[PDB]
């Protein structure tokens, strides 16, 4: 029996701007996982958002800041003309048109508003623990509404003291959008948003160290001033490929013989695997649950440049077809759709 | 009665960085051992340090090298911008806010400065004898201040001529962070750097001879080493479990029927065995270094001849002789923060006033 869901997106920026982080990939993929099982999914997101096949409603207003002004002590903030506030006002007005509302935003207000809704509200958490106000908002809604909080990885849940009461739904992609490439060029890839402390420096240095050009995909929003700054490695070393569509990304990415992930503190690793692309990552966080050591990638001692360069040297030992097979066996929409229902359908009753 | 302590951390690297050596683990546990009795503990440590729930002040400067340029005759060295010198200058400024200052650094300077403080200074010596200058600084402090020097193990103490005048406070960890697992999977564990010259081959070959998969926890630096192990021992034989947090390590380690410890002697101290015991996991270790003072032969593990396959295999086959609940009971009785807090009070309280 089929149901009607409303997905409320992140307020940090529009779907398609590259500003929403992983939610920009997760939300449409989870929506498609559910509609392919006969459900209706509508999306509510900031003005300027795009979404190819689904009902979308947008609301103008000021985007939610990402800044941690006081570390773990920074309060929740609602600016004038807040888009987050307007999104949840709009959701509330139409709450009776849906069986369940799914919140994708890492913010205090949707959690606080949950008992103010008659329609059930579930929360897919996309970040690890960052602030006291957020930890407490999530815990409160866990206490009141068991099973209402999901996460993407065990590593992510482990950053929360209540992590064991969060349901882990893992990750998935629309694999039919991604082509397997068995014949890479002698280049490395990096995917992410192009901004300070995103690990991008570690990747360039390692790829350079290894004698391989680094190709870089993502959104440029310290532009070019953070970016051009980094031609302190030379266009010798690093090659911006743009912020592109998924189809452009997969055909470009699949040409790399490896993907470097060098973050600090999920989709991107799977996107590489889906193209046949092994992943070299710091042994830290979400990649530990995606990559199979020495089979679909290399998980290496974090912050060690010789480790990255050693791993780059062992890329051709990895079977690209295995990487693609792992993506199909583990990260399909069809299985994510099953996990979504096991999570959300009990929340209806 | 409750007292106020200042802990001055190691200069070799920041707390919570991975680059501070063993003090990185001991200092937070010994601090917690005292604050769980109602004492106050504040910490001075290098810039970049991270230490939850305790007053922490950090100090900029160059880390202290651990390397000796010519062995036991190496002088004590103070580089420009020495973080060690700055730590002890700052501790001196604030000495009157505390009843006692506890030094964790293995260095000449804090011992030399002890008579220049009005507040008592105690010293936790975390390593064995390495230099004439350090031996003599410790011996002089013992002569002037009997009872002011502690060590973690009796082995360490005996590398010193005055070892019998040092107090041994043993080891502890935060057992509340470790879950007792009475029902393991039929697997073995091994914890350490996934790198050559770590005894990992010894552990793999013995687990394989015994018919048991080996799970490993630790950092991989050379991916070709991983392939070399696959080529030598087969594509199973060793299963990578992660480079993971303390809470993740204990959840996975607890699932093993035994922990194999095969380190070279210079790395055979000693705390991973306590983590295994705290999970109910008996320990099979080479019979040298720190494990000799952790494991009870034939009760909480097996202490075996080093570098001998047959001895590891024989021990793996007697894991069933060992009571996992007894392993946990020994951790609670011997290696708890509660036990450590009592030893610290017995050591430090007579030094007050």
Image (tube, coloured by chain):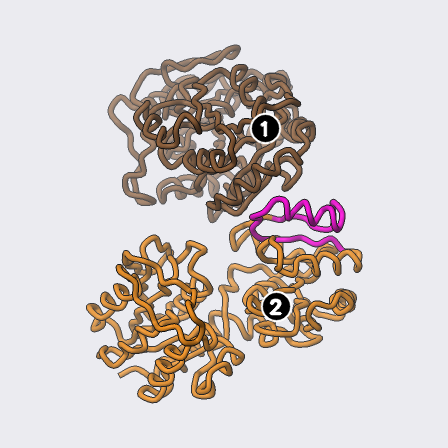
Chain colours: A brown, B orange
Residue at label 2?
B328
Magenta residues (range):
B212-241
Instruction: Examine the image and state in which quarter residue A172 appears.
Output: top right
Q: Looking at the image, can residue A159 be seen?
A: no
Residue at label 1?
A257
Q: Element type at marker 2?
A: helix
User: In the rendered view of the protein, which quadrant contains the C terminus of chain B?
Assistant: bottom left
Instruction: Name the residue: 37% across, 76% down.
Output: B123
Q: Position of residue B302 (x, y in %)?
A: 70, 72
Question: Magenta stretch containing residue B244, yes or no?
Answer: no
Farthest-out residue, front: B70
Label 1: chain letter: A
Q: Position of residue A203 (x, y in %)?
A: 46, 35
Instruction: Name the residue: 34% across, 77% down.
Output: B122
Residues at marks 2 and 1, CA–CA distance in whole angstroms: 48 Å
Q: Position of residue B212 (x, y in %)?
A: 76, 56
> Badge 2, how many Cα within 10 Å: few under 14, some, many 20+?
many
Label 2: chain letter: B
Q: Looking at the image, can residue B326 be seen?
A: yes
Cβ atoms under marks 2 and 1 closer than 8 Å: no
Above or below — where is A135 with respect to A323?
below
């Amino acid at each position: 029996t089929a149901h009607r869901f409303l997905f409320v997106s992140t307020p940090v920026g529009p779907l398609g701007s590259g500003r929403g982080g992983g939610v920009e990939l997760t939300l449409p993929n989870l929506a498609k996982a559910l509609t392919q099982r006969g459900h209706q999914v509508s999306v509510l997101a900031p003005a300027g958002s795009v979404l190819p096949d689904l009902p979308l409603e947008t609301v103008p207003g000021t985007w939610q800041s990402t800044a941690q002004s006081h570390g773990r002590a920074t309060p929740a903030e609602i600016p004038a003309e807040s888009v987050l506030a307007r999104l949840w006002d709009r959701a509330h007005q139409q709450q009776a048109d849906f069986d369940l509302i799914l919140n994708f935003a890492y913010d205090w207000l949707p959690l606080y508003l949950t008992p103010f809704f008659k329609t059930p509200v579930a929360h897919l958490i996309s970040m690890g623990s960052l602030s006291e106000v957020m930890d407490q908002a999530i815990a409160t809604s866990l206490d009141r509404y068991p099973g209402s909080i999901a996460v993407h990885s065990l590593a992510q849940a482990a950053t929360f003291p209540f992590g064991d009461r969060c349901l882990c739904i893992g990750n998935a992609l629309d694999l039919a959008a991604y082509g397997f490439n068995p014949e890479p060029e002698p280049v490395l890839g990096w995917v992410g948003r192009i901004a300070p402390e995103k690990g991008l420096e570690d990747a360039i240095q390692a790829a350079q160290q290894a004698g391989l050009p680094l190709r870089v995909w993502g959104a440029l929003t310290e532009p070019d001033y953070w970016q051009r700054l980094q031609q302190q490695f030379g266009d010798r070393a690093v090659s911006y490929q743009g912020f592109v569509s998924t189809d452009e990304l997969q055909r470009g990415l699949g040409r790399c013989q490896g993907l470097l992930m060098t973050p600090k503190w999920g989709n991107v690793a799977i996107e590489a695997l889906a193209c046949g692309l092994p992943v070299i990552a710091y042994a830290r966080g979400g990649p530990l649950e995606i990559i199979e050591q020495g089979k679909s990638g290399w998980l290496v001692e974090p912050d060690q440049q010789a480790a990255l360069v050693n791993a780059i040297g062992q890329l051709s030992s990895l079977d690209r077809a295995y990487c693609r097979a792992q993506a199909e066996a583990r990260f399909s929409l069809a299985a994510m759709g099953q996990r979504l229902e096991a999570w959300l359908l009990p929340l209806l009753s």
